[PDB]
Image (cartoon, rainbow over all chains, first blue to last red; front, side, top):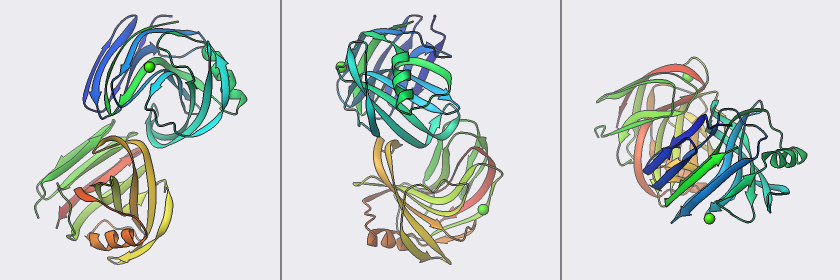
Length: 178
Length: 178
Ligand SMILES: [Ca+2]
Ligand SMILES: [Ca+2]
């Protein structure tokens, strides 16, 4: 498509984010959560390509296609990689997509910050069983699998490839496209 | 004692906070959560006096003694007033203190921002059954009641009289001391 959205969220500590036309770079050393990455203002069904490096020296680190949905309000993740990630919520099932199987989870965030202000909403997460830092993510396979398990999505809002972390340091240089 | 701590937390929208030597003032119109108020760097057992106004035109609004504790990490509230507050967690019991009864709740915040960075910790809340905007809060009565129900506190960290809100507008002018 063409990246037209820059996800830049951070609460504290050392987070050096460098967005670009074809991707982004991040170096961090923080105790606080941050979500940075690049993508699109309105997500679609187009298979998303990502690639590069993603190192987590310590703490929690996640590399994933991240996004939102409205009516209902939904925060979703399709984790291609994760370290020291406190698996929260309820497992719903699985979906085999793009070279590996993903365990699907549903979680709820009460009075949490969102694109609609602080609200309560659900999370639809797909965690890859075989972590990678390079590949393609056929997003429709996840949306279909989510819908079939009762994980209902609304209108598509932004959709980015993001790195999220806290409790340590690490770095990532990723190329994003679709 | 003498106010030596200024609680100033906010995530977005219109929040006009004005701290002072004997209290604070706030006018807001936001969808995002904010916690502002004044107090002390290290909380004690000293009965806290508060007084003034606290109007909530719309959305969620809470007037309460707010604080933290370390080892274990604990966020506590002693709500003297609240509007449209999504009572979250588990009721534990009650405590009669300073002219009214309070319903005690215990809740857990997973991967939430804290004084120790983003962490998972419990909340000990005392919600006054008869809301007020002026009075004294004998904090020990709450700490004793909390301990007796298994709500264990650690080392005292900051302790302020704060106003917290989201989803609307309102204003508050409070005098703080102990
Ligand atoms: Ca990895
Ligand atoms: Ca009131």
